[PDB]
Length: 93
Image (cartoon, rainbow, N blue to C red; front, side, top):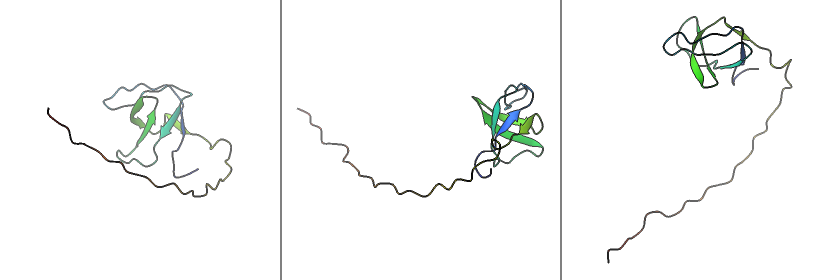
């Protein structure tokens, strides 16, 4: 439960009553980005076609789905790439 999304649940339904504010209802997960920095006592997140700055309160940090099973995603190798020709020599006759 760290580095990579946060996960929040909108307590009450708030309306974007500002310039670049967000709009969401209660019972809606708020993909808050615990990285973006800006305002002091403000929290920025990204919801269904809704992205703005909201007050740190309305939302309530949710649990990591009742504890999580530490998974270790081993590293995998990817195949190479191949380029192709372009353009060409047109004519005029």
